[PDB]
Length: 112
Length: 112
Image 1: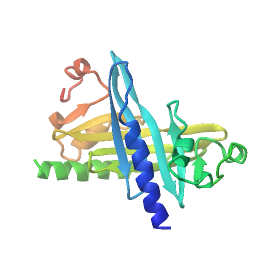
Image 2: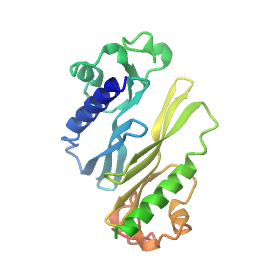
Image 3: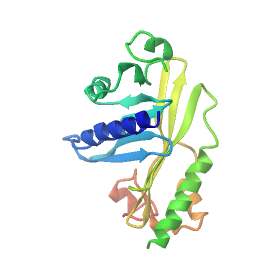
C-alpha cells in the first residue's frame, strides 16, 4: 500500500531514468527529467532544436494513481507495459492512459 | 544567487499554480502540476479526452537555469514574460526558450 507505492515509485523512476540514456540522433535536443513525487507524476521530455524547427514534447510520462501505474504517453518504440511487468509489476496494476476506458476493457490491462 | 533562486522558484510556482485554476471548456481534461525542484523544471499539463480524441500536452513549462527563467512552452494567450515582470522579475533574467538564439537577440529578452 505504502510499500507498493514505494516499489512503484522506485521502478517507475528506474525505467524512466533508463530511457534518459538515449536521445534523437537529429539536432540539438536535450532529454530531461521532470519527476514530481508529491503528485506522483513522472515525465521525461525532449527540449531543443532541429535547425529552426523547435523540438518540444514528452517522450514518456507515467503516473502513479490509486496504487496503479498509468502510462500517459510513450512516443518511443518501447513497450513500457511489458518493461514494467519485466520489473515484476502485475499486469493489472498497469493502466494504458492513452486508451479510452472502453479500449482498456479490450487491450489487456486495468481499466482503472 | 540562492535568494534569487528561491525568489524565482516561488514566483515560477505561483504563476503556474495560478494558471492551474482554469481548464478547457471542451471535454474531460484535467490540468496537472509536474514540479521538479531538484532540476528546477516546472510544468503544467493537459491530460484527458475530447470524446475519443486523446488530449495530452504541456500547457506551460518554465525552467530555472543559471539564475534565469526559461519559458520552454506556452500554449495559452497569456504573456508569461510580462506576467513574470509584473511579479518583479527583471526582463534580462527571462529567456524565451522557444525562440532560436538568433531570434532571442531580437525579441527583447536574454539570449541565455
